[PDB]
Amino acid sequence: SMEQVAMELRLTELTRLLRSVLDQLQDKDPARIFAQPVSLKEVPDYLDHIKHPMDFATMRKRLEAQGYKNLHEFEEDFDLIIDNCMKYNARDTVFYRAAVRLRDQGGVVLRQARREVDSIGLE
Ligand SMILES: Cn1c(=O)ccc2cc([N+](=O)[O-])c(Br)cc21
Image (tube, rainbow, N blue to C red):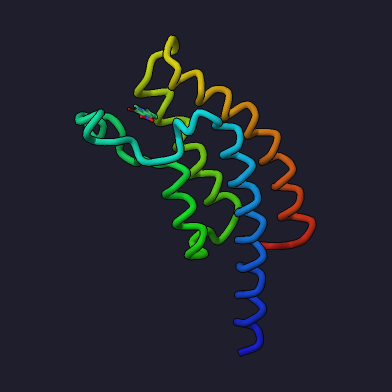
């Protein structure tokens, strides 16, 4: 149907916007601490601590499968990256501190993304 095509066009446009957002967020992680899943080889007990691991590569895979239906779903995954890190690592670590900085600098990007998704009507 034409309605289904229209819905699919909206999803494609949301995906385009979210791709730009993801690139901007990842730029705020220059050390690439959050680029890939936490290695169970360097951190073998990780899954005993963290029940829903997340990272930028995993988000990008979901994104390109058009697996984010709205901005909220995308933000949920971004918040997992930060929140997982601030639980597993102590405040005096380069990991925790990278998550704080990513959260802070990311908030700015996400604030304007919410305005764009709303005003253009992408969900
Ligand atoms: C425990 N842990 C986190 O919580 C978040 C990121 C992270 C990255 C690496 N890394 O190598 O990039 C390692 Br070993 C551990 C990490």
